[PDB]
Amino acid sequence: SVKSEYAEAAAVGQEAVAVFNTMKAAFQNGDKEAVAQYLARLASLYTRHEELLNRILEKARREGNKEAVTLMNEFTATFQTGKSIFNAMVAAFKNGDDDSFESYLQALEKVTAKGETLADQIAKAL
Ligand SMILES: Cc1cc(CO)c2ccccc2n1
Image (cartoon, rainbow, N blue to C red; front, side, top):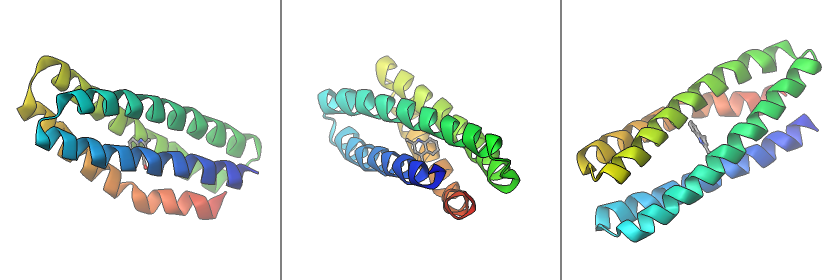
């Protein structure tokens, strides 16, 4: 169902969460070789999450589930904020700009934490 597909999507989100927090530790430790690898891993995860989310939204639309569509339209808009900040973080790492990397990192955390109440509301709406 769309609901199982959302639980599948949620798990990918939590995996990216887990990797993100291991990457932060590595960055703080200066282990750039680890950071580079975790940034690759997070890119692949977010790319997969984004695609699963699109499929869920399209299915909610085909189902006529107006409330779930409203919530998913907002949730995906927030996701794209995250993706933009993530991409800026990756560029800061490429550039050696640790000040920008720290900034982007904390912003990506706050953006993600905010969007959590909506993430749970979608689960209940589908
Ligand atoms: C993989 C992933 C998961 C979540 C939520 O857990 C996100 C939230 C905002 C932006 C990007 C995100 N990327």
